[PDB]
Amino acid sequence: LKTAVFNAARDGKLRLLTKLLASKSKEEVSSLISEKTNGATPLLMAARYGHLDMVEFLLEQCSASIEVGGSVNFDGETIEGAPPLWAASAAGHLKVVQSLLNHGASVNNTTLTNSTPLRAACFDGHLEIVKYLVEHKADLEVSNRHGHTCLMISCYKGHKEIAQYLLEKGADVNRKSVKGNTALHDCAESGSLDIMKMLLMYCAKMEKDGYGMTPLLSASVTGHTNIVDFLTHHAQTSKTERINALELLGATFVDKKRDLLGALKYWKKAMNMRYSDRTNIISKPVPQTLIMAYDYAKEVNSAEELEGLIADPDEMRMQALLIRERILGPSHPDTSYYIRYRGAVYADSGNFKRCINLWKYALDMQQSNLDLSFAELFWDKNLR
Figure 1 (cartoon, rainbow, N blue to C red):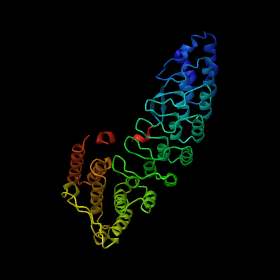
Figure 2 (tube, rainbow, N blue to C red):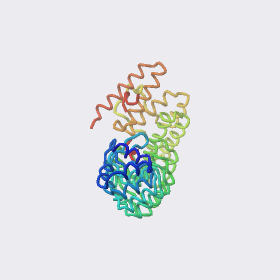
Figure 3 (cartoon, helix red, strand yellow):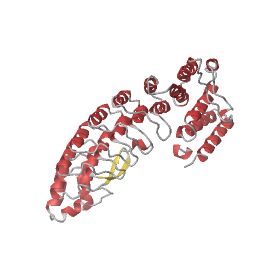
Figure 4 (tube, rainbow, N blue to C red):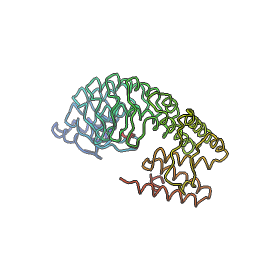
């Protein structure tokens, strides 16, 4: 019967439920209401699926599970510890949110990952819920267990109106997550140029994160040329930051975009800057040794060495690997990742020796730089 009660509440079948409940006691209803059916409770399941009248009914009986967190499903994932207010917020149910709050639900109660209802509404961009939680004293600066903020997830998701509202309400634009991520990096990674300019209206400062990435280098890693174009013309980036960002973006064009002509265009820009001031030429750093996995290649160091690259796609592919290891280094996950992808392409074309040398090298890199495997192929930020 406790299972019939939950399934009735979960699906908003309020007629059925009131029959099963009218024949019973008042003290025994509060018990069947608070039953952990499949990790959830009736109120939580009803709030998660928007059945406004059901939850208004469940609370008229026993308003005593209103803060109990449980299990809800979103996008085929399972969220642990989510109170009802959080689930109504995550799923966009404005009036269930308004109701739960009128019944005294705690606007700050979180999931097990310390996600607030406000963060949940920011994730899928429910602007009107965001405004209501904030007008009802949501704390803008409570972040999840990784230190990722409502502002950061708004920037990462591309929600311009939400990010703007949060900033008008005094959200701190310069917060840093545990890994050193600022909202400016979320903008760089999502290609959200409008939001990035909005953050710079508040003097958001460009910083390195834990990978040593500025937001400019984040946009080069992820391939968003609108951010790279904007930030390489911004006075807060130095000449050499710009050169490296353009060379890295070229490498991204080779390995991620499979666009060799795009790659060459950014490598020429960068090579121009390297030689623009003849009194202070900025030539390529020199690595410790040549590398067998990279076919012993060497980065081009002159405009002339560049023009004789397009007809040699295989030279460009080694240029990209060298560029990425120089600028990102062995600890960034993309370095070993694109070494393995490069080996995979050589394998598919029958060059198994080249493949194996690349894969041996990427494995050595991972193991000698310790605190996306082949099996798994066969991240934090997307947490609600």
